[PDB]
Length: 179
Image 1 (cartoon, rainbow, N blue to C red):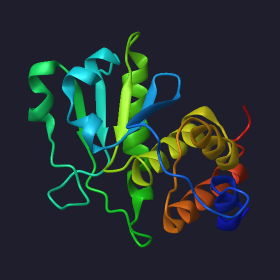
Image 2: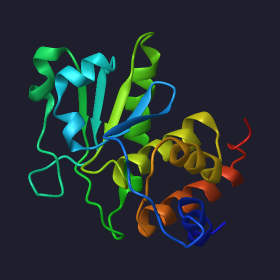
Image 3: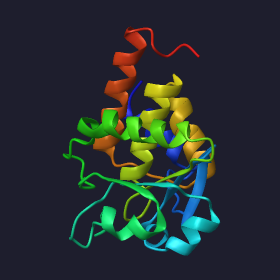
Image 4: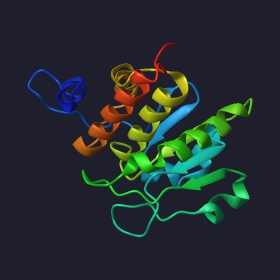
């Protein structure tokens, strides 16, 4: 398993990634991935039945989404923010466990649905969902990435892909990828 193998799963014949055609998509049952605009549109969130929002790009830069728990208080939506940067050197894997635990809490509610979003819904938030699928649903990285990519055009940066590969190797050795 290499980063290049994941690049290939994200790429077409000519070697190009694609770009999200919709502001958000349900990538696995009751888990949505989306962009900044959907995060900040509470009426649309309610029509989608979203009860829980994980902002994987929390902050005040043009690469972040400047929301917080208070933004969602009136709506009754439950919030967690992760201040991640979309760069190859950023250590997103430090947040995989707390992200996975938040997703699990959302899904434990009978009618719970979680939006995991960042600025573009392209790199940061899909990486967290792929890690959740590996850690909590026992899917190997290729099948987790492939199911998300089947449902939304994503492109985690190569640092995030490397982090997913390191996770996969560890979980495989521990015998934790046997669904």
